[PDB]
Amino acid sequence: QALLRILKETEFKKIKVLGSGAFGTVYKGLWIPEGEKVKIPVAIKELRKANKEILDEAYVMASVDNPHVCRLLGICLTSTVQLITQLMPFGCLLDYVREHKDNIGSQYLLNWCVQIAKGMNYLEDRRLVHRDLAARNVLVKTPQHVKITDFGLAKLLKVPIKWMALESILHRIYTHQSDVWSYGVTVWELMTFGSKPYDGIPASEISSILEKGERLPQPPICTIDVYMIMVKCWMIDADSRPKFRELIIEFSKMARDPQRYLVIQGDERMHLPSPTDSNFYRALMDDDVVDADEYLI
Ligand SMILES: O=C(NCCO)C1=Cc2c(ncnc2Nc2ccc(Oc3cccc4sccc34)c(Cl)c2)NCC1
Image (cartoon, rainbow, N blue to C red; front, side, top):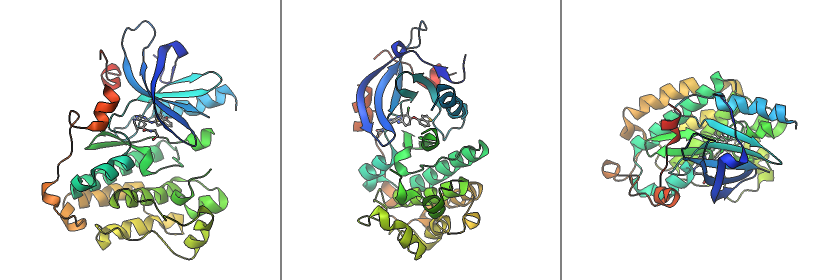
C-alpha cells in the first residue's frame, strides 16, 4: 500500500536496453509484484549519499499525481539505485517530432506546449525544481498526450549547458524560473522538429554568447507571437520570465486558433500513426500483460 513501492530484485526484470544517459541506463522490462500474479510493462532506470536520503527524495517523485507528469512507481536499492515507472510506448518527444515531422500539425505542437506547461506548473506547486527539462525528457503516452519525466535526478545525484538558464550556469542557481528558461528551449526543439540548440557552438562558449544577448533563432514555422514567448523565457532577469501558469494561459489561447500562430505547409491534412501503425510502439510491446494505469486504479 506504500506510495513509494520498495521492490525486490525478484519483482522486476530488465528485458531489453532502451538507452543510455549521463544519469543512467534505461531498460524496457516487467514489474511482477510478489504474489499479486500480474505482469506490468515498465521502464527501469539504473543510476550510475545514504539510503534514507535517496528514499526521502524519491518519495517526492512517487507523490506526483498529474496527467502530464510521469509518476515513480517503485525503487530498488542494492549496489545501485533502480527506478521503476510505467512504460511509455511511443518513446520520447524529441525522437517523436524528428520521426513524424511531415505529419505534425499546429494543433498538436501547441497542445504539447500546453501539456508541458501544465506538468511544470504542477511541479512548481510541489516545490520540485526539474533541473533538466528538455524534449528528451518529455515522453509520449499517446500522440495527443505527453508527460514530463527525469525531474529532480540532478539533485538526487556533465551539465546540459545548452538548456540551462544563465544564472544556473554562472551561479548554480536553480529555481522554477530557471526551469522556465529550459521550457523555452524545449519549445524551440518542438517547433524546429528536433534541431539541436546552438548546433556547432562549443558548450564552453555558451555563457558568453548568452551574455552578449544572442539567443536561439526564430523557428521557420513560428509567427513572431510564438517566438516572443520563447524569447521572454530567455530573459536575463529570471523574475521577468513568464510563469508556468501564464504559459498555460497563453498557449491555451493559441491552441484555440492554431493556424493563426504556426505556419505549416499542408497543416490541414496531417495524420499520426496509431498504436497498431507505430513501428516504435510495436518494437517495444512485442503477451499476458496489464497496464500500470489499470493496475493503479
Ligand atoms: O528511450 C527512452 N529513454 C532512453 C534514453 O533515450 C525512453 C524511456 C522511457 C519510456 N517510458 C518510461 N520511462 C522512460 N524513461 C525513464 C525516465 C526516467 C525514469 O526515472 C525517473 C527519474 C526521475 C523522475 C521520475 S518520475 C518517473 C520516473 C522518473 C525512468 Cl524509471 C524511466 N519509454 C521509452 C522512451
